[PDB]
Length: 149
Length: 149
Ligand SMILES: COc1ccc(CNC(=O)c2ccccc2CN(C)Cc2ccc3c(c2C(=O)O)OC[C@H](CCC(=O)O)O3)cc1
Ligand SMILES: COc1ccc(CNC(=O)c2ccccc2CN(C)Cc2ccc3c(c2C(=O)O)OC[C@H](CCC(=O)O)O3)cc1
Ligand SMILES: [Cl-]
Image (tube, rainbow over the protein chains, first blue to last red):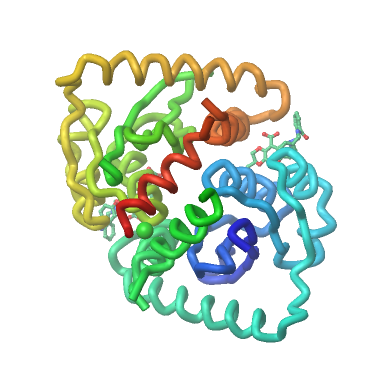
């Protein structure tokens, strides 16, 4: 579970926000892309896996699971690519809630930047630093450090 | 110590590679940009600080130290913006060596992608996972986790 991430794609302002959630901590990375292609998704995962020890990614949809470019990225980065079937129905609700939370934060910062990508990164910052009391950022580091040790 | 980062800018293929190094661990994040403007640098720092607990950034040059956009991002993200004067002359050699290491890795992967940005992210991955025996990625997590506890 320290190495398990879940992809999530949401929409805003006619653009796509691609999110990777670290399941055990709720920590996230996100980017704005024009559309969710296999190439965009592959590049995003390459970035993520160079930054955190990504063992497994539950893809966000069947097209990214199928994509040979995505599978090639997962091969490259040593990632086990898996489906995102919510065998635990709670997975669904957690992601849905996270998307609503993220959109709320983006609205709260939206006027502090011209470009959506800027607001999304501000939203990533606020989400990861929010104490719920540890933050998601604190949680992911402790989880992973415990695993190293 | 756990919160201190150093910016570093290097060039390849007529493009700019912007790097942030976590001083204590040698862990890096990097991006390819067309040119190193205050705005690009500001956006890069906002991204970094949403992802790791960035307390202090030593800027890579005087233009980024001066830039009001960069100062505004550091204000936004709660980052202490500092100069990058190598009061310890070893700082300067470490960065030069890091740039040469990264360019070497980029050369080793260059034929595995059309776009330089892809090769740079592959280089980030290889650099952070390389056991020197712990990796830079292991070290940053352990350093920050020790600080949390
Ligand atoms: C990480 O994924 C992979 C990493 C490595 C491989 C194995 N190598 C090859 O198959 C290969 C080799 C040589 C030339 C072209 C290719 C095929 N390419 C398509 C690889 C590629 C993918 C995503 C990208 C790329 C590029 C690129 O060639 O640079 O460029 C930037 C965009 C940016 C996001 C966007 O613009 O959508 O993401 C496959 C996937
Ligand atoms: C992160 O730094 C800051 C974040 C926030 C502030 C306070 N808010 C404002 O001053 C503000 C408010 C409203 C409209 C425009 C602005 C002024 N902007 C210039 C802010 C901005 C900076 C860098 C960017 C931006 C944008 C943007 O407006 O979205 O957009 C993407 C590019 C991507 C990199 C590149 O393309 O160079 O980086 C300052 C710096
Ligand atoms: Cl954080």
